[PDB]
Amino acid sequence: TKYDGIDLDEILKSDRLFNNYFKCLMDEGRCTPDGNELKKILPEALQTNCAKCSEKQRSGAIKVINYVIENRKEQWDALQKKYDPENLYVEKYR
Ligand SMILES: [Cl-]
Ligand SMILES: [Cl-]
Ligand SMILES: [Cl-]
C-alpha cells in the first residue's frame, strides 16, 4: 500500500509524514492526492467497515485506522469525533 509514492507503514511511523496526513484529514492543511482520497473514504471505512469500497481502499484505510487507534491516541480522538461521532468502528467492527 502506498500513498503519494510512500509506503504507508512508513507514513504511519513517522511523526512528520503522518502529521501532514492528519492535518489533511482534520481540514487544517492541504491534502496530497492520496490524502484526499483517504479523506473521502474514511467515514465509510469507519461507519460501514468500507462496505462499498474497493478492497484496496479498504485495506489502506483499515491499516491507518487500527494504527492510529493503538499508537496515536489523541489524533485518533480527533479523527473519531469528526468522521465517526457514534464511535461505530470501535463498537461494531473492530
Ligand atoms: Cl499518487
Ligand atoms: Cl502511490
Ligand atoms: Cl510519537
Image (cartoon, grey):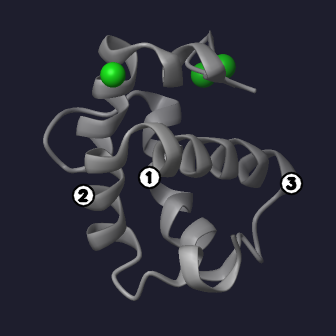
Q: The N terminus lies in which quarter of the figure?
A: top right
Which element type, helix, strand or loop, lies under badge 2? helix
Residue topped by disc 1: 39
Image side of residue 43 versus residue 79, left or right: right
Instruction: Name the amino acid type tagged 3.
Output: Glu
Gap between marks 1 and 3 measured at Cα: 16 Å
State the image quarter where residue 20 is shown: top left
Gap between marks 3 and 2 measured at Cα: 25 Å
Q: Which mark is residue 55?
A: 3
Residue drawn 24% across the image and 58% down it: 78
Q: Quadrant of ligand 1?
A: top right
Residue topped by disc 2: 78
State the image quarter where residue 10 is shown: top right
- Residue 91: where, in percent of width, then height? 57, 84
- Residue 60: where, in percent of width, then height? 69, 42
Which element type, helix, strand or loop, lies under badge 1? helix
Residue drawn 47% across the image and 44% down it: 68
Residue drawn 76% across the image and 65% down it: 53
Image side of residue 71 versus residue 93, left or right: left
